[PDB]
Amino acid sequence: DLDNYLNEMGEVTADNIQTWLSGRILLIENAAQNIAINPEPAAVASLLEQKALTSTFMASYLGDATGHFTIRPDAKMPDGFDPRVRPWYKGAESSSTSTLTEPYIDAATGQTIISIATAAKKAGQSVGVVGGDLSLQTLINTLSAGMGYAFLVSADGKILVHPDKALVMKSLKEAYPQDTPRISSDFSEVTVDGKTRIVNFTPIKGLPSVNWYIGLSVDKDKAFS
Image (cartoon, rainbow, N blue to C red; front, side, top):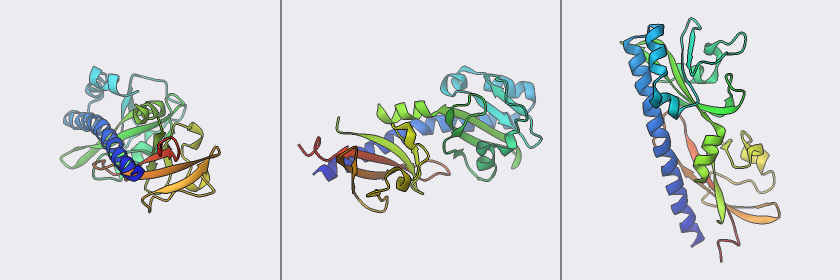
């Protein structure tokens, strides 16, 4: 009924964001691979400056175990900036594949972003970590391109991307303290803004390092009709 429409639409939404992310992950992997061939700083700079990267990401960059950092487009980083302590770096150094960060505060722009990152390895030997930034707004736009809306939630129940920006990086409990939607169940009903809503969770397949779900929240009335 409404159930099968929401299961279908969860699946299409999840598949869309997977295909959207997977090509961007491939660009960052490709970059880490090319950086590994020749990690010299002039060659690194030239690779990161290319249009395919600059038109896809806010910026791409390489940080290494000495703390050296190269970012394109170039940007004045904050005083004391050390790439090694940033969440994209730590997440990628402690992974055998590519990663995606949860939202965090961009050191370059001050905006909330996520990052795709992967370790650049020559002959099994790490030359640094390469990352590319995507804005939260870009993600919000991707999940919204009727009866309801889509949001992105981690498998811990942390809301990562939501059209209501106030709920970003709130747990499901904190965001919906009364009648908390459960990832463990097929459907959830919860009252918000004085309406009853039906909530669905669909896993996103094929992302490296992360286990994230598409949430669908729908009006019980404007779709039952």
